[PDB]
Image 1 (cartoon, rainbow, N blue to C red):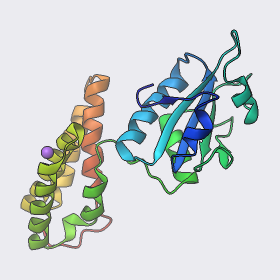
Image 2 (cartoon, protein in one colour):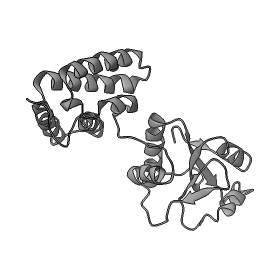
Image 3 (cartoon, rainbow, N blue to C red):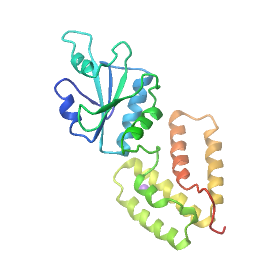
Image 4 (cartoon, helix red, strand yellow):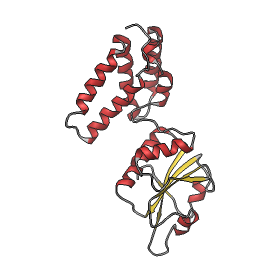
Length: 228
Ligand code: NA
């Protein structure tokens, strides 16, 4: 899958031991289907979020020299019940396995990382360096809102990743609209977005809307404390 590093008997231990954390799916060689697609989606997500996590695959072949059988056997991977998902903590000796009962989904894989490492794969659309300064934005004073607009506008112009540049536009719109009209903007925009999301929409269009809804979520506050 895109971003998934496929490892073998020669590369596995050496590569795992060079990253702070690795998540490895052991499966048949040339895997396919729902769990693999989830692992693919996971690779994409993890990649957008961090550089300290290796996303890797090991394909155990049933043919010829049985490449990677020894590797599978080192970790006692149940080859009657592929795929098997492992998380390694910086070397090939210190690891945890994904319980065999847990469905191999994008959500469950994100959860696996966050339960077993200091790493966090955020929501699609989010930008961590924006989020870290935006807590409680709707409630802070106008001058501090304007300072943050100027700051994140400067950050946006430096953004080199195309998705982050697009997602930054939504952050800025929301920052400006909330500064202009106040927290009522959250409800307005949530209803607009949900009307769209409730229409007949393609998967791509849904993903676009969800990214807007995820960025807008950053602006929700538990309590409105600023005057409207
Ligand atoms: Na931008």
